[PDB]
Length: 129
Image 1 (spheres, helix red, strand yellow):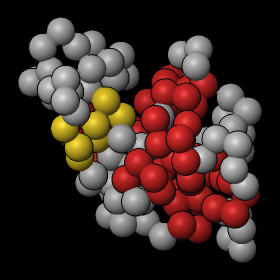
Image 2 (tube, one colour; image 1 turned 30 degrees about the vertical axis):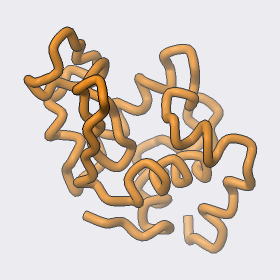
Image 3 (tube, helix red, strand yellow; image 1 turned 60 degrees about the vertical axis):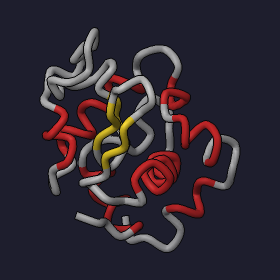
Image 4 (cartoon, rainbow, N blue to C red; image 1 turned 180 degrees about the vertical axis):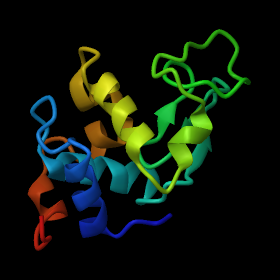
């Protein structure tokens, strides 16, 4: 599913991400924009052979199981396929654990490089929330 910007902002709010660990909804919408272009089915193989899955491009090295990332953990206790669903519950539940891991949203490379410090409120500007 390809979410619209405000449609995702709403979903993310409904699932408890708005200001989770102190990150405003605009931060999450911006991370999703640059990780997956709001497409829940996004996948991208990393050079280390891990893969990133879903709206927030969560990596199989640590967070989910895809059966093809030797040495990995599955700290969200989910199959990576669950991170590709139209329903964002699994991606949100996992992101909450990732953002709680000690480095905040720096875990999302696209957030660090393209969202951090910027006017992230632009991402929810205009949305009925």
